[PDB]
């Protein structure tokens, strides 16, 4: 017994809508990179629910995933299961949660059942001050309310303000003038490329940028972006990911094994027709399992929102930065717009630059240009030839345009000389990093092997 | 530890504790257990750290015990992640038994392929009611491609984890193309040509390959004659979509191809005297070798290309060389979706589904009217000017050009040259098949190539 | 009840599920094209399905589909009772004067059942995967396989012309 | 007998002929298909200047339940705010 709808002292509260947030989280681990975005702890209504999401936090940072089983042994040691509900309660929220369906909808509700539940209990204690002033000289009452209504704070992670300054950056600034450790006179700050030519324009790839490769199609677009990720996995020891959306997994390696090892592709195109080079094969096969660096995933239905749910489940369960390469981003589709490309690029411009600033990762994405370049008598790409795109001319931080003369001509003195036009450049000059196209082995060697320098 | 019927994800903990104690002691069971258990399988994050150390050392020609487990792990710094030798020694209690080890490589296999079938039945239910699928018919097209790619070699997961171990071995296992066909009848589905398959090296087996030709060029002549040399030759259920012809008109052409009879004979001066000898010859070899399937409906959205080609790959293995004649007839559900963006959702749903089924998808398109105002009338790349989105998202492109349809007294009569413009994993060239079109068959025993110097 | 109860309701568009039944009941020459894009068991609630089956072949079988020809065929079939009564037939006929945009309400009930049946497929794959009975991984990867392609949906004999029947060789 | 009054959206100005057709009240639904005597109102000297229907408005019937339709014209003195007698010109 209790009286009717006139009883409304429960301000809001959502307890039926809460157990189906822990319910599917009890039966899934792939969706903690979502509900933690929009439900943090101390939103739930009941105190036994807070200790569950309390120890769902430490196990996700320790890496140990959560079912009923790995939770209770992690609540046996910490002195819990006595005040969190008991081992029957975890089965009460496992038998009575049939929904293996949707958590991203009950998570928004507990957020907007708590903000309202807190702003009621703000106005029961600011409007308690006039209800009982016991004397604190009401000008000094006025900073209580600035401390009450702004105590709604959400400091779950890194950079914010308030506890933030410029001197709090200047320790991190002298932290990154702590170079000259590995390269006493030689090289680069961030992640390498591994060439005598490219490391004096970009000075390596900067550890939060978004370097865009662009090229006329099949004029050397994945010859570059795998050669560079070849050279940046023997040189970093980090999870250097790949999203090959265009090629299949079996066909990625059947150029990289011709490039790490420099066996010719005719020895891997047909049947292998040498037993000298098998050691050249098996050595670099062993090198590539000496270091378990290069990753691959060959999706082809990639929204740029489901990219984040791969490339964060590599940099969390393993090492750090790597080099999150994504091949050929027009094949990434956004189904939200289904519109002109001048908006479907704009979600990829605003999400790849929101993945290169969580994980501090140089996302080497790839694009191509429109066919009206093929009538411009100076075929070399400039920024005014990405007319299909829209916003990618601005959000990128390093834009490399790959001409190649011998694929658009046959009087080419640039025979095997792929050139790299740096279209955009944020933090340096622009220019021409001319390389030696030796894609017989899927290679880009350096032009100071040949005679001249990068004019 | 109460044992009850609850909703728990299926995994075993003792069984993972059972295997790791065996390979800690033994370095000789590694002959066995490396075959049937791979990484990404064990539940807790420290467990596959131990497994990679078991792999990096065993290739390095160094043993495995509780001693060397500490050695590289402090050269790699991961030792306090797994917990140091405080926890590895608790795995030094597990098994003196070198038996049930493959049986413990079986249960941890068995609780890990069911466990790869809860993150497919949540990659569907979190597409539904939170639409990253946005229409119903392309919400089923992602409800299939996370399911048919599971029903596979079953060392396959959904997508996302592929450590370079698990792709290097499946690369060398796909360079086991070494004892059969030492000649260049290359790994792809054959076309039946010893002029083509030196320049294409077969139709590479996961590639969207685009044919284009003018009208009055014989486009479906080549596309069935290539399939008829790839249906009685490579054992796989070759599906065919066709909209330029109706269903029976295709079969009236193929019987004029296989039986080498004239197609004027098939309706005028009918199947009468000695043509019965050849037609009843190829109505037996085609009768039960259940390869060529044909479907010819008119409204072919790129949703209902997949959802017809999934069944074909379901009932069989499926390297069905899908021939889709006349791609421009494929009509997307959105109509104000215009021709600059109609094909750009077809260019990126054939290439994105010539990849799951491992099928070399031959699709067919055509070049515009402004082709016919040039002098060198060859179909080149810059004359696919309907959309320009398929010119850049294909793998092999063959532009057909028959000379005597556009010229009269020149001596290249009956010499169709299949121009290979965009060749990705190989070099360019120029073929010359012999247009024997009264039966619509091609090969070059009468070979129009110079062949002398 | 509070309005967090929008949880077990796949979208199913009852307003778009009534304007089609008011579309055919006033216009008999729309069941030729509407029944193409829309089939039964896409209608969410039990009265709407069987009413659409009560038009069994009643395009050319000699019955212009109004409230009169329905009510006589209802009771010789036997369902003038509380699977619609007769007052709801007036709610389906006279309250729904709906226009010549039934083909706009046709694609809704095509596309709010596919998204609906992809929840019970997304349940019955998963709820089996928590209770493993006496059947192994060779069962569940082949029972999740077939249960997804039970949602083509069903239209007609298609997808396979020649050799399969092999008769489309012999139809030539 | 309930006279009700309503307005049209600017989708009509997309058409060249700005005569108010029946399918311009469909944009809210329950007014186009629950109307019994639609009487649209046109007037040309406000939409033009060189028209000779100046001050003479033409009520267009768009639907009628129990009779005919047509084009009933009325004259209107542009000072008194009074619509007036017969259909000013000849036809
Ligand atoms: N034997 C060879 N001779 C010359 N070039 C080759 C050879 N093998 C491969 N290539 C080159 O490899 C390149 C691969 O193209 P790529 O940029 O990967 O295409 P995409 O842009 O679709 O990724 C082709 O442009 C081709 O020129
Ligand atoms: N009796 C015949 N002699 C020569 N060619 C024929 C005959 N019957 C049909 N054909 C050819 O069949 C072809 C139909 O194949 P298709 O490739 O669709 O045509 P196109 O080459 O115009 O695209 C036509 O080009 C036509 O030349």
Image (cartoon, coloured by chain):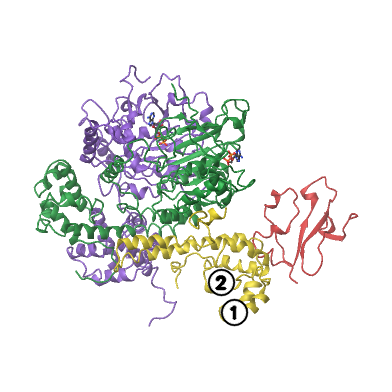
Chain colours: A purple, B green, C yellow, D red
Name the residue at 47% across, 55% down. B307
**Quadrant in the rendering for residue C17:** bottom right
Q: Badge 1, how many Cα within 10 Å: few under 14, some, many 20+?
A: few
Mark seen at residue C77: 1
Mark seen at residue C48: 2
Q: Badge 2, how many Cα within 10 Å: few under 14, some, many 20+?
A: many
Q: Is residue A77 above or below residue A327?
A: below
**Quadrant in the rendering for residue A399:** top left
Q: Is residue A283 above or below residue A147?
A: above
Number of numbered tags placed on the structure image? 2
Name the residue at 29% across, 52% down. B155
For residue B46, say whether it is visible: no
Say whether disc 1 or disc 2 marks the residue closer to the N-terminus: 2
Name the residue at 67% across, 64% down. C29
Which image quarter is the C terminus of chain A in?
top left
> Which residue is at the front of the view, B355 or A20?
B355
Q: Are marks 1 and 2 in contact (CB under 8 Å)?
A: no
State the image coordinates of residue B87 (x, y, percent, origin top left). 13, 55
> Which residue is at the front of the view, C160 or B88?
C160
The chain containing the residue under callout 1 comes to C
The chain containing the residue under callout 2 comes to C
Given this view, does label 1 or label 2 mark the residue nearer the observer? 1
Q: Are marks 1 and 2 on the same chain?
A: yes
Answer left or right for B235 relative to C82.
left
For residue C117, say whether it is visible: yes
> Which residue is at the front of the view, D45 or A88?
A88
Under circle 2, the secondary element is: helix
State the image coordinates of residue B381 (x, y, percent, origin top left). 51, 32
Under circle 1, the secondary element is: helix
State the image coordinates of residue B70 (x, y, percent, origin top left). 11, 47
Q: Is residue C54 above or below residue B383?
A: below
């Amino acid at each position: 017994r209790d009286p009717q709808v006139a009883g409304l002292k429960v301000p809001p509260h959502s307890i039926e809508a809460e157990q189906s947030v822990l319910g599917g989280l009890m039966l899934d681990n792939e969706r903690w990179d979502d509900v933690a975005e929009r439900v943090v702890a101390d939103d739930f209504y009941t105190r036994p629910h807070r200790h569950i999401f309390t120890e769902m936090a430490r196990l996700q940072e320790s890496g140990s995933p959560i079912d009923l089983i790995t939770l209770a042994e992690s609540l046996e040691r910490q002195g819990q299961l006595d005040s969190v509900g008991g081992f029957a309660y975890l089965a009460e929220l496992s038998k009575n949660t049939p929904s293996a369906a949707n958590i991203s909808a009950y998570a928004d509700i507990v957020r907007e059942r708590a903000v309202v539940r807190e702003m009621i209990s703000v106005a029961n204690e600011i409007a308690e001050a006039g209800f009982d002033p016991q004397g604190r000289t009401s000008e000094d009452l006025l900073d209580l309310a600035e401390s009450r209504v702004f105590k709604i704070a959400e400091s779950r992670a890194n950079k914010d303000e308030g506890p933030k300054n410029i001197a709090d950056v200047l320790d991190a600034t002298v932290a990154r003038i702590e170079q000259l450790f590995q390269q006493p006179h030689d090289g680069v700050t961030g992640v390498n490329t591994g060439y005598d030519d490219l490391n004096k324009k970009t000075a390596g790839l900067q550890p939060s940028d978004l370097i865009i490769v662009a090229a006329r199609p099949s004029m050397g677009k994945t010859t570059f972006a795998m050669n560079l990720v070849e050279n940046a996995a023997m040189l970093q020891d980090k999870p250097v990911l790949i999203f090959s959306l265009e090629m299949p997994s079996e066909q990625i390696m059947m150029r990289s094994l011709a490039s790490l090892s420099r066996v010719d592709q005719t020895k891997i195109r047909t049947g292998q027709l040498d037993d000298e080079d098998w050691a050249r094969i098996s050595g670099t096969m062993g090198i590539l399992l000496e270091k378990r660096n290069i990753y691959i995933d060959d999706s082809s239905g990639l929204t740029p929102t489901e990219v984040r749910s791969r490339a964060r489940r590599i940099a969390r369960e393993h090492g750090g930065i790597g080099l999150i390469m994504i091949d050929y981003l027009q094949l990434m589709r956004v189904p939200a717009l289904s519109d002109n490309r001048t908006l479907e690029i704009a979600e990829i411009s605003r999400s790849l630059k929101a993945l290169a600033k969580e994980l501090n990762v140089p996302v080497v994405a790839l694009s191509q240009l429109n066919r009206s370049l093929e009538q411009r008598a100076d075929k070399r790409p400039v920024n005014s030839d990405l007319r299909e795109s829209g916003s990618i001319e601005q959000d990128a931080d390093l834009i490399m345009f790959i001409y190649r003369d011998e694929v658009y001509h046959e009087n080419s003195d640039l025979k095997g000389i792929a050139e790299i036009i740096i279209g955009k450049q944020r933090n340096g000059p622009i220019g021409t990093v001319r390389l030696t196209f030796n894609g017989q082995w899927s290679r880009f060697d350096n032009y100071a092997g040949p005679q001249y320098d990068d004019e």
